[PDB]
Amino acid sequence: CEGNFYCPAEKFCCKTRTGQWGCC
Image 1: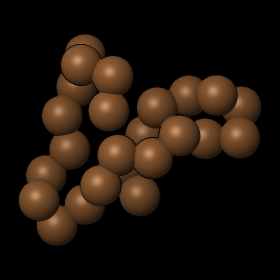
Image 2 (image 1 turned 30 degrees about the vertical axis):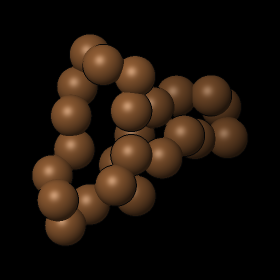
Image 3 (image 1 turned 135 degrees about the vertical axis):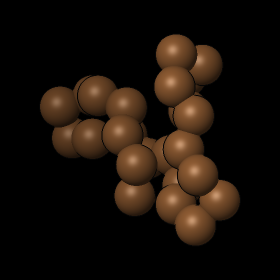
C-alpha cells in the first residue's frame, strides 16, 4: 500500500498498470 488507505487481510495491496494503488 501507500498509506492513504489500507486493504483487509483476505486481500492484498497491488499496483495497477496505469500506476494506481489498488487491491488484488
